Image 1 (cartoon, rainbow over the protein chains, first blue to last red):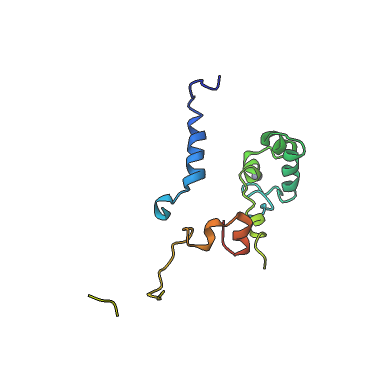
Image 2: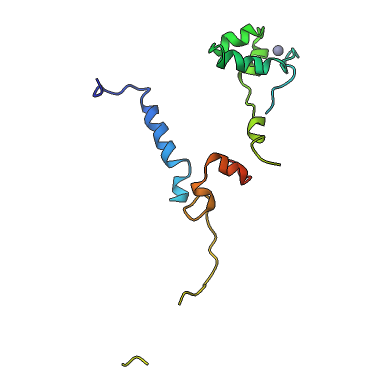
Length: 30
Length: 65
Length: 38
Ligand SMILES: [Zn+2]
């Protein structure tokens, strides 16, 4: 079932990854 | 930073209860609400003291001098 | 037309945490020794 649709709580797992990588000032550094 | 001695609202000593609370969580796996209550922290004024504490001192200690 | 090195030009301020900054490849414990806040 690894191809099951995503829930609403799962969007936070993506947001976690966005910030784990980019941080809060990616614009300034990049 | 560093556990408040005495709850602001009623002044029940809360200074002793810190390590004991942190222990009832790691060692006893217990949920926050039971640990607080175990420690006799019944009034929410007292509960908020421990439950919402941020022991910044521990980061502060990480610097050498 | 017949034919008959590396020079310093200036000091450029670095933005902290950038590639050129020391703190970029810095671990948590590293920053603390450097008296910086992680
Ligand atoms: Zn109280």
